[PDB]
Amino acid sequence: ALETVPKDLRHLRACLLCSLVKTIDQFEYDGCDNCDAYLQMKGNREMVYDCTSSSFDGIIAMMSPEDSWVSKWQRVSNFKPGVYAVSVTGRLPQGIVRELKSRGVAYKSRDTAIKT
Amino acid sequence: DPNLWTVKCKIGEERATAISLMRKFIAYQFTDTPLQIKSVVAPEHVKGYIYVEAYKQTHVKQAIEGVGNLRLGYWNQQMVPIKEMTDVLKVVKANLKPKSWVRLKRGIYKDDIAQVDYVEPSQNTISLKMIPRIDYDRIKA
Ligand SMILES: [Zn+2]
Image 1 (cartoon, rainbow over the protein chains, first blue to last red):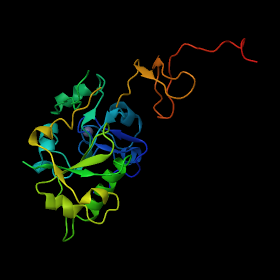
Image 2 (image 1 turned 120 degrees about the horizontal axis):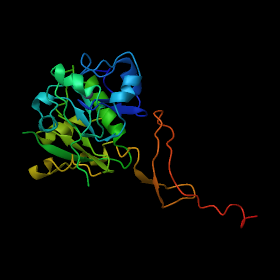
Image 3 (image 1 turned 60 degrees about the vertical axis):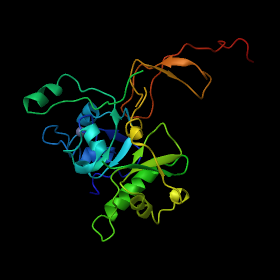
Image 4 (image 1 turned 120 degrees about the vertical axis):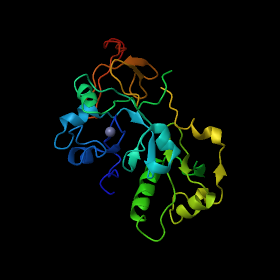
């Protein structure tokens, strides 16, 4: 859709769960689409900087996760089409990751990149 | 499994090409001439060409018609082996973490190592640790 596509290249962040790369305005207005009920991101800016982090590289034009090897490798087949990444460095604090497992949400590390 | 093709592009324009392709796909997806491309990879370390995922070469050949940026890489479509389908996504250590060491390019402390202290969420300025090198106003006039 036209709401997930980034509008301006400047000031762009990325999520850590599904690695959704968009513009800050969309994050403040729309927020994480693939995970909204379990993240509570729409309607505030503090949570955006809390969970999402700008420390990420790599961009991929995901359009058909159901039929794509990159989606299977990145484990993003059950997500909506959009502009994702391949390496998001960061880790959520110890106050939000706890409730994810209780509600049936497996928290995995999307930082597929290597260290040294 | 789908194949990954390579197409040449200009140096310094990779995110703009990606967003333009996304806009074109979103604008020409409910028409009689859709795009069969699966995805495109634009690594940050590389600068000068981009990748594209598709089964046959005709797909990407007919999918990049009309764009004025990929005109250079239109008469040749190279195919990479299947073993190179996993090294493109690899990244060697983004690169923004507090209490880390970074170097400077401009200023006076050129080609010197430093250390990060605090990061501003505004994404406009960042602190830095460094030992002064000035002469304390004794040599200069
Ligand atoms: Zn996410």
